[PDB]
Image (cartoon, rainbow, N blue to C red):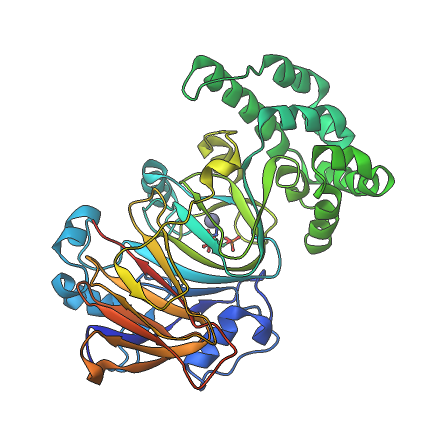
Length: 440
Ligand SMILES: NNC(=O)[C@@H](O)[C@H](O)[C@H](O)COP(=O)(O)O
Ligand SMILES: [Zn+2]
């Protein structure tokens, strides 16, 4: 039992939107790692939490089952290092939380606070806002993924406002006119034209979000009818849109998210391996797929639709920046990672412009196999295997060699060089790992 490289058994969340039972990647990974856990086949397994966030612990199975949070707290210098202790301001915890999500139904229409709102929300309602942190995040598609992310460009929103009768009726023609006349493009971010564009978009969004629920139920029914009788109205906005509306209405009948997500937010698809980042306060809602997520350590979320959980429409309306930048600006270029070398066919850094984390992906071909060696990184890491199997060890110390099968999660102490090996008695699954880490 090395304290440098060691297995962790991570807790999970059974949120409603999760894939059910053994069809969930969360359930699969949990059970794989600890075959003694009985998967409840009737239950959703939505999120695997890998981290030191107090809401869900990770336990070091060969270090007397103590929690990762406790182990950090007992030895901050060894587990975090002074650079991470100083930059992020804690001796107790990781500044990131790393997750697997396995999504069956769309998540809440949601936004996470920045630092200022984080502190204010936590102070005003610590029950619903359980810490004071911000939560920028990143998603990496493990299977093909869809989600909502950011307000659509203004010309698309103007078109939608003019051509979708059920939305136009909720907003009212005077406000639709005010919005469509008033917007000015191009507008540089920060310019008075931009400021005014955002104020107009906030007026439209607030009018929608504060509409009486019985009105929303009446208009959603008519919207749904219209996707059937006049699909082309919807396809002219975006070709996937009538089917989207139909599919989400089956999940959450007559939900306000049919207006506020489907009509106002970009519908993003990510192919497997593609990724996107979300700065704090970007509005979003993940629709489908299995993903890796990494975020600043927080569970603050303001929700406003597609959920039975706590909704706070007024905070949502007030906090959003109302940016309408193209969503392509937050799809990430994949980068090379010099500090890893070997036989892996993919070795890919996902490093968004967010201080609290990066993620390194490693993939070995099923037939080719081989070994990859990664230098010690200047901060704590979590590694998960999402596919295939192999072995993991501290480089040059064969006594630390351990099996790493699908779903196994390991902590790696700062400075510790790692060597991965693909299983060789095997030629059918590409051994694949994701490692979340941070460096000042
Ligand atoms: N974008 N994804 C996330 O922020 C997830 O990590 C959080 O856990 C979300 O809060 C999950 O969505 P619900 O609150 O259950 O609607
Ligand atoms: Zn989120």
